[PDB]
Image: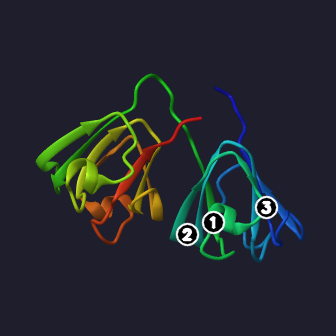
Amino acid sequence: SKTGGKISFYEDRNFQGRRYDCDCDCADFRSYLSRCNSIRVEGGTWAVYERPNFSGHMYILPQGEYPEYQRWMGLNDRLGSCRAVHLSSGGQAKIQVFEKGDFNGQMYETTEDCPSIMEQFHLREIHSCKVVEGTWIFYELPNYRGRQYLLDKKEYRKPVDWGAASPAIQSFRRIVE
């Protein structure tokens, strides 16, 4: 239970340059680092945002070492805020998705990751879904590519409820550690 996540950001590639270490969520770390082109995650998972106030592109980083921003699929080396993602275990993660908003339309339930929603469910978009686990990732393009959205053990009734400006979502995966 009592763990201790920690993430280190470096201004240059190969963990060179000024470094900044964080052990909790930080809404604005720009005062400690003006840019980050590489990151090291010593423990725990973390969500990073391109602009302050958890806004702009969002990416989930599992424990590991990333000697360059491209290793984290970063679009650039701009990061204004970071939050620690908490993982929930317990037993078997199950997700239910609905073809229309407000949990309406045809419903499909699965306990496995989905690389291509259109190939698996023949659906071009997702407007609502109820996942009860704690850490789920949704991706805008197939094969877990494009902008990613982090879902919690809550129910999303509208597409904008998961931070997306469009109901376009093509793949999703469960987070485990």
Labelled disc at residue 117: none
* Residue that appears at 19% across and 49% down: 98
Q: Is residue 157 visible?
A: no
User: Alpha-carbon neighbours of circle 2 within 10 Å: few (<14), some, or many (≥20)?
Assistant: few
Residue at the outermost front position: 119
Judging depth in this view, the residue of 28 and 8 nearest the camera is 8
Judging depth in this view, the residue of 138 and 144 nearest the camera is 144
Secondary structure found at label 3: loop
Disc 2 versus disc 3: nearer the observer = 3
Q: Quadrant of the C terminus?
A: top right
User: Alpha-carbon neighbours of circle 1 within 10 Å: few (<14), some, or many (≥20)?
Assistant: many
Residue at which label 1 appears:
81
Secondary structure found at label 1: strand
N-terminal label among 2 and 3: 2
* Residue that appears at 72% across and 37% down: 4
Residue at which label 3 appears:
67
Give left or right: position of 96 versus 22: left
Residue at the outermost left position: 105
Residue at which label 2 appears:
53
Look at the numbered discs 2 and 1 and tell me whether their residues touch, using CB distance below 8 Å.
yes
